[PDB]
Image (cartoon, grey):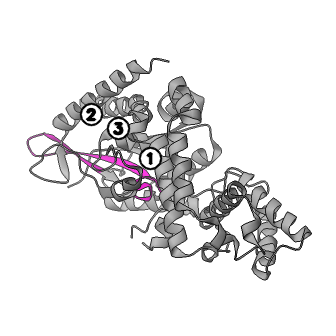
Amino acid sequence: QTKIQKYAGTAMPYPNRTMTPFYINHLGRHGARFPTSRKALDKVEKVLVSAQQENGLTSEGMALLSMIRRLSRLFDGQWGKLSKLGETEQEGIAGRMIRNYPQLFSNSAKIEAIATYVPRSINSMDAFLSCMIRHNPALQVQRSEGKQYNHILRFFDLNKSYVNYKEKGDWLPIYKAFVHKKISPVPIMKKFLLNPEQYLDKEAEEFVMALFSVAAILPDTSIPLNLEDLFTLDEWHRYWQTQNLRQYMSKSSAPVGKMLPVAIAWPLLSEFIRSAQEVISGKSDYQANFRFAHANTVIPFVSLMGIEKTDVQVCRPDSVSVYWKDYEISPMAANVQWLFYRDRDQRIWVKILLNEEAAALPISTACFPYYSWEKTRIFFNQRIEMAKKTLSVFNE
């Protein structure tokens, strides 16, 4: 809703969302979580504590230092866990699904859910399932999780060329150059430190970036404290621009990545198609397949699907934010749903929802948002073929 929330990017909480299908194919990111790393917090504290020792803090800086120490105590032992908000986000997603399509989850419908080995994903799965079971205890439920699903849910860890690109690829200097251009650390640090001009540009920038990082994740934690007012709206905008680019180039369809970050997702697109074909043919009789994973799962998956906008290949870094927006693709609890329908002539239609809003594909249909499954499957198999050919060039 608000521009300020949007600028949290992938850390934005899941936005407000207040015939009948025969099958639902789902992928969801875990819900709102605690920060995963204490690195940024420790950086901020270390700078403010060192300043306090040399009498370099303003009044606001002292108050910030106390706030940071408080957060350090609250975050302790909570790193990476799903928060209460994260649980409620999943309940809302499950609740709207049951309310919108009750016939599908009626009687003794069968559902399967899988998750990664990461606890926040498993807990997200469980918040979702508990809501399904609460609404219909007569559901048949298969629940599993773990590294057995790495190939489809954590492909971003398994591809050596991609891991290399992620850690040291040519996207790196472009990001750093972009940050230096967009983020002016002095006016921000002036609020907290006496003589902020004494700080070297690199330390000043690392401090400011770490502070943004702490402020951005705070709304996902359910802790009733807020740090958005540490920065102006313009500074948030600029920060978001940098993180948006970082995500785009490291995880999506940026020309610098050569579609490597997108191509690695094909086994999941392949598995989505297989689960659907098995239900359609009667080989499986599941009414829904749910999958719980990560932003790094959702982003290239959505790009590989070719949902309009999300796989744009933008050559100019400053243009990326106009065309590709991470908070529309992968907020907390980001999810893709394929809803399958059978018409009166037994033709199969599919509707794609991205965060519960109809998505477009670059194929035609006479009845948007519904697409012919036949056409859609053909398009998706071409995407998988393109993925494999891309991967054949970076054969590790």
Work out whether residue 154 or residue 292 is closer to the camera in this orientation and state it: 154
Q: Is residue 217 left or right of residue 259?
A: right
Question: Contact (CB < 8 A) between labels 3 and 2?
Answer: no
Asked if residue 92 is positioned above or below residue 337 in the image, the reply reads below
Cα distance between the residues tagged 3 and 2: 8 Å
Q: In the image, what residue occupies the spot 42% across and 42% down?
A: 252
Q: Is residue 94 left or right of residue 83?
A: left
Asked if residue 269 is positioned above or below residue 329 in the image, the reply reads above
Look at mark 3 in the image and give the residue it sits on: 304
Q: Quadrant of residue 393?
A: top left
Q: Quadrant of the N terminus?
A: bottom left
Three-letter code, disc 3? Leu
Label placed on residue 380: 2
Sequence order check: which comes first, mark 1 or mark 2? 1
Foreground label between 3 and 2: 3
Residue stretch rendered in magenta on the structure: 325-352
Q: In the image, what residue occupies the spot 36% across and 55% down?
A: 319
Foreground label between 1 and 3: 1
Cα distance between the residues tagged 1 and 3: 13 Å
Q: Quadrant of residue 172?
A: top right
Asked if residue 151 is positioned above or below residue 94 in the image, the reply reads above
> Does 341 appear in magenta?
yes
Cα distance between the residues tagged 1 and 2: 21 Å
Work out whether residue 83 or residue 110 is closer to the camera in this orientation and state it: 83
| Crowd band around label 3 with a 10 angstrom C-alpha radius: few (<14), some (14–19), many (20+) | many
Work out whether residue 79 or residue 328 is closer to the camera in this orientation and state it: 328
Three-letter code, disc 2? Phe
